Image (spheres, grey):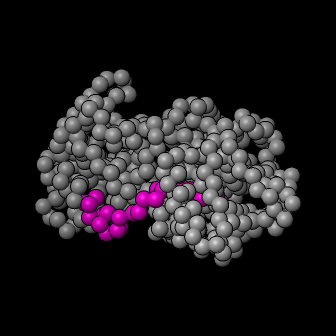
Amino acid sequence: SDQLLIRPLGAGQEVGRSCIILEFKGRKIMLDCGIHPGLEGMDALPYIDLIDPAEIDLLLISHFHLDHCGALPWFLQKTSFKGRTFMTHATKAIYRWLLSDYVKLYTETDLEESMDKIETINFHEVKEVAGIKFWCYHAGHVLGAAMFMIEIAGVKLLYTGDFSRQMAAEIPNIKPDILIIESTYGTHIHEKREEREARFCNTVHDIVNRGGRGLIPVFALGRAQELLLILDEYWQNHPELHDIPIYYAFKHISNLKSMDHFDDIGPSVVMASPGMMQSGLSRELFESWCTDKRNGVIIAGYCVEGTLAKHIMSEPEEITTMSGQKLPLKMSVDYISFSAHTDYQQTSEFIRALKPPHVILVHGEQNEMARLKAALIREYEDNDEVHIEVHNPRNTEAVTLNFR
Ligand SMILES: [Zn+2]
Ligand SMILES: [Zn+2]
């Protein structure tokens, strides 16, 4: 029998800095290498100290979001890592653009110097490195997102990275022995898409109707363009809103460039990034509008601990200006999901289709992940013909499996 070891260095019982180590029959693989959106500098990095970069044969990146590849430039240009790295074409493209803008660990120089060290891979195409065969499936979630299936000595493991089944994620016909899957939404169930878009539109409407400024923080394109389509349509069907502008930083939406390139007048809707409001325009606008109860913000994506958007949802009496000033939070705050992750029914169905004897949960808040684990254990705790062990390792903790 051969022993297989899986160990999160990031995203273990948390969302952020996804980086999971896999060790089997002499090979070592790293799955993702991102940073924690809610942490600063070196503290926002996975615990790559526990390992020797030089011993990593393969590095696979699921998608372009920062919590999955935010720390790559650093890893590639500042450690003893001399292995091979792979991404899908689109992922790599958006990588340079996205990580660059992130540069407001490494520098613009390092990023451009890592591009050469990153190989691309097409979907449904088998690649081989050090006796490790791998290929990817569409993950849904975002453009270019991939779920890597890995095979070593006949043992197969599927890593979902981040995925959605609502472009929908493919369900592999090839059954893996091990499944590493995201736990973002835990046991939550997503509300009907139509009810979601209606509540989103009615909330935006309420804000501008009372003379308010409505802020909609969004990232690169995790749903940005989709929301613009929803609002524009709604505006078309409501002539009484034609004089209320909608800016994006279509027939009713105009593009904005900066807080210095737009007039902040009467009621309006402004969709700006970053989605989690740590800095940038979304944060500046929030700081300029938070004291007026007529205004409102609508968080349309999942927000990691440590971020302003997440804190705002706790409905604090006051907020902290980037400059350190204290401002009262009077604008309304609403949360309507559009982050594109699977909910419990979708995760459950995915796992039921593949029936992996071993399921390893990552990328989920501790408590959310614990309920998912329990609910999954409960699902197969009844039938004795399907044995599935669910693991929820903390960062640094290893899961050990023996094969053959
Ligand atoms: Zn993601
Ligand atoms: Zn993620």
Tally of marks: 0
Q: Which quadrant does the C terminus fall into?
A: bottom right
- 113 or 204: which is nearer to us? 204
Is residue 216 visible to the viewer in this orientation of the structure?
A: yes
Residue found at x 54% / y 37%: 103
- 137 or 112: which is nearer to us? 137
- 233 or 137: which is nearer to us? 137
- Residue 224 in the figure: left or right of residue 346: left
Residue found at x 54% / y 40%: 36
- Residue 174 in the figure: left or right of residue 303: right
Q: Is residue 181 magenta?
A: yes
Reply above or below: 17 against 122: above
Residue found at x 82% / y 55%: 3
Q: Which residues are magenta?
A: 179-201
Reply above or below: 255 against 77: below
Q: Is residue 53 magenta?
A: no
Image coordinates of residue 237 in percent, x first then y, are 19, 68
**Image quadrant assignment for residue 195:** bottom left
